[PDB]
Length: 10
Length: 444
Image (tube, rainbow over all chains, first blue to last red; front, top):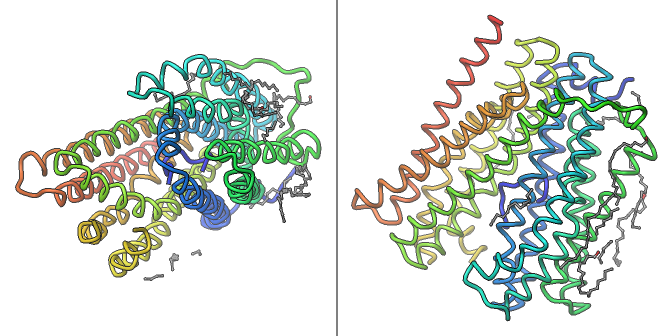
């Protein structure tokens, strides 16, 4: 989500 | 003094890793669940709505990278103080981090707001749709401080072994966003901008909880007050030494993600991009439990480093790899065995199955390098984490992916293989670097 940058959008 | 989280950080490292990582893996999973849900509502809004999200998306990740970076630098610094039994120091770091959250958060808002117009115009977009992107950008940029504040507050909680309330803050935020999303988008007919307001409102509510804990209830191990307060350049440097390279690590991935796409285009075409995007999105789902373990590793090794206990630091670091390794084995085995079933539930089918049969292999050796980076941040050496991240994603991933496509007969297969072989090498190098750093700690 917001606390983890590397996800990213999905 | 004291709290359950502090006792957890100061107790058994194996017990600390388990009780801290589990709430973190859950909090991040709910966040992922939001992205999957939001990706469905927006997808049925039209091409103009998806194009608006894509324009602000790199900016959004930029805000997140800065927020999460300041957060991990906060959690790491606080964990080390608590381990060293520096109560006044831990209190002082928390205050410094909150002041930085205001400085960083508001700066992002006032910097991007007047620049967000020409930025969208420069990305080959006339509005029309670019005008819709601005309205979507305004809402999220308006709560840039709220974003950074929530990451700092979460960092403070993680710093004192309070993964429970940290999990709660993540669950409340993403959970509320999941609720408001269909209401704002469809029910109220706000469209894609409604998703922005839903996110903004969910962040604000999260902040109300965090502020209540930190400023009203004041039931945290650290004491937060501006009386009388004293600016510390050493604390600022200690936070930025982890925080700044943490943000640059995300930039490295984003740049690497750009080049991996370009290689997938040449292979390739829009068909190659569609397969890579789908295969990568599914594969990165198994990354979530590893990230939660990394957040725990930083706090536990940090507290152990503050206690000057290399044995406790090494134990927690190696134990985190062990668990994450076991988890990924289940994840990789699941994905490869049920690849056609997974590909069917996310949809180029033939290429996607083969991609899922080859790509997620790297998740196996991933914890070896990711926990090393996590403990590098725990001891306060974020530069090593940055170098390791750059080496893994730019030199290894992009490097091997570019070779197996331009120099070998392999087409799209050369892309997955390159990514797999690349970071597996970086996993070995990272792990070896970790053993060297620990050996140096014993001598020091």
